[PDB]
Image (spheres, rainbow, N blue to C red):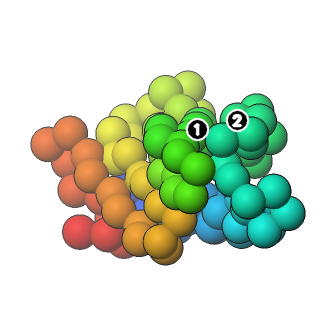
């Protein structure tokens, strides 16, 4: 239901943010995101977290809903290195975003 979804969407925002800080620290140590091992991302119980885009100086993190633990969620959440968070679903609003 919408309540469950609203909590899970709010908490995966924290997960994405935590990964983004980790990558910001990594960028200052290395000067690039190209060498980052995409299997060092912190996951979320209700969303699988991946690097949808990675370039030397920028990245986009993406959270896709877990179809087992978060069945019925279609909203995909992104966060880029610029700090812009965004969410969109499939003919479904994203509580806490729209």
User: What residue would you read off at disc 1?
Assistant: 50
Q: Quadrant of residue 35?
A: top right
Q: Which mark is residue 76?
A: none
Residue for point 65% across, 63% down: 20
Residue for point 75% across, 47% down: 42
Quarter that holds the C terminus: bottom left
* Front-most of residues 57 and 18: 57
Q: Earlier in the sequence, mark 1 or mark 2?
A: 2
Of badges 1 and 2, nearer the viewer stands 2
Residue 62 pos. (x, y %): 49, 46
Label 2's element? helix
Residue 46 pos. (x, y %): 59, 43
Q: Is residue 5 left or right of residue 50?
A: left
Q: Is residue 24 visible?
A: yes
User: What residue would you read off at disc 2?
Assistant: 38
Q: Is residue 4 visible?
A: no
> Do residues under tags 1 and 2 come within 8 Å of each other at their CB atoms?
yes
């Amino acid at each position: 239901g919408s309540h469950m979804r609203r909590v899970r969407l709010s908490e995966v925002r924290t997960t994405l943010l935590h990964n983004a800080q980790t990558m910001e620290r990594y960028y200052r140590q290395k000067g690039t995101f190209k060498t980052y091992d995409k299997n060092k991302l912190k996951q979320n119980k209700y969303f699988n977290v991946t690097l949808s885009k990675v370039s030397p100086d920028h990245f986009t993190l993406q959270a896709d809903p877990n179809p087992t633990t978060n069945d019925g969620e279609t909203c995909v959440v992104t966060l880029n290195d610029g700090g812009t968070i965004a969410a969109s679903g499939t003919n479904q609003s994203c509580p806490g975003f729209d």
